Amino acid sequence: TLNEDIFLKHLRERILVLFEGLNSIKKDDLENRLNLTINFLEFLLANIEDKLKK
Ligand SMILES: [Mg+2]
């Protein structure tokens, strides 16, 4: 069963690597979208405050 053990252990590692890559990709995409929304809200806040000082 040696060949079986090698294939299964490598397959486990491949699954873990796939999960690690998927989580990295999702984290980057989430960071991008969060930065967009946060910048939008900061621009809105700054514009509102500039509109209030006048
Ligand atoms: Mg790993």
Image (cartoon, rainbow, N blue to C red):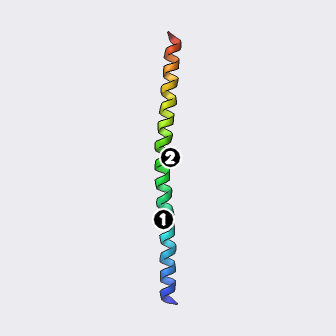
Crowding at mark 2 (Cα within 10 Å: few <14, some 14-19, many 20+) = few
Local secondary structure at mark 2: helix
Local secondary structure at mark 1: helix
Above or below — where is 32 with respect to 25?
A: above
Crowding at mark 1 (Cα within 10 Å: few <14, some 14-19, many 20+) = few
Note whether ligand 1 is within 8 Å of mark 2: no
Q: Position of residue 23 (x, y in %)?
A: 51, 56
Q: Where residue 37 is drawn, which disc sits there? A: none
Q: Position of residue 22 (x, y in %)?
A: 49, 58
* Cα distance in 3D space between marks 2 and 1: 18 Å
Q: Position of residue 30 (x, y in %)?
A: 50, 46
Figure disc tally: 2
What residue is shown with label 1? 18
Q: Residue at x 51, y 34 (%)?
A: 38
Above or below — where is 48 with respect to 26?
A: above
Q: Residue at x 47, y 37 (%)?
A: 36
Above or below — where is 20 with respect to 48?
A: below
**N-term mark: 2 or 1:** 1
Q: Amino acid at mark 1?
A: Leu
Q: Position of residue 17 (x, y in %)?
A: 47, 66
Q: Residue at x 49, y 20 (%)?
A: 47
Note whether ligand 1 is within 8 Å of mark 1: no
Above or below — where is 35 with respect to 25?
A: above
What residue is shown with label 2? 30
Q: Amino acid at mark 2?
A: Leu
Q: Residue at x 49, y 31 (%)?
A: 40
Q: Which residue sits furthest top?
A: 54
* Residues tagged 2 and 1 counted as in contact (Cβ below 8 A): no
